[PDB]
Length: 309
Image (cartoon, rainbow, N blue to C red):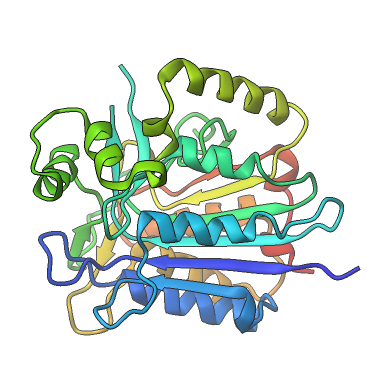
C-alpha cells in the first residue's frame, strides 16, 4: 500500500511594497531541501508558491487554498498519508475576541476557521503538519488542542542583537490595503474581501454567522473522533514572529531557522512535541521573545515529525 507525502510551501516577501519581508522565500527553499533529503518527499509532490516578481504561481489566497485543496482529496482513509504545509509571511488578527489569519500576497485573508475546515476534510490516520512562521500564528487551526503554549507550559534573556522585522501586520494596515483595491471605505473587512474575491474569500466572510455556527457544530462533532491537524506556530496568538536579517539574500525567519537547527543537531526521528520544545529552547537562548506553540491531539504530540522512522 503506497503512502503519499505531499507538500505545499508558501513564502511571501511582498517585494517592492510597504510590507516587505526578506527571509520568507529562503525559509521555503530551506524547508523544501529538508523534506526532499531527510523526509523522502518527491519533487512532483511539492507545490511552491512564492511571490518573487518573476514567479509563475503567486501565493494568492485562491492559489494557496487551491494547493491545500489538491492535497486534500488525495489523502485516502487508512493509508496514513503525510501532508505538509509551510507558510512564511505576514500574519494578522481580525475581530471580545480576535481571529488569527495569514496574509497572502493579494491580502485574500485565510483565517483560523479556514484551516479548521481544511483539517476536517481529512480522513482518520492521515496527518496535516502545518508550520506557520508568521505573526499571530498561534491558534491558526481553530479548536486544535494546545499541547505547548501559554496554557500548557509553566530569568530574562537579553534581547537578540540581530536585525529583526515583524511578520505581523496591524488590522488597520490590512484594511487600508483592501481599501486601496476596492475604493470603498468601511470598517467591515469582510465587505472588502467579498467584493474583491467573491466565492474565493475566506469562509468566515462568505457565510452568515449562524450558517457558520451550524457548520462549526458539525466539525465539533467530528473532532471528537478524528483529529488530524498538527500546527507548529512561530509565536503565540498575541505575539509576532521575527524576520531576521536584511535584503542581502541571507535573511531568514527566526522560527524556521530554529527548526532547521534542531533538525541539524538531531538526525534521529523526533516527536512533534520534542521539536517544538527544542525550537523554543533555541529562540529563548538566542534572545528572541516569540514563543513557538504546538497544537495537535495527544496521540500526534507523541508521534514523530513527518512520520520519520
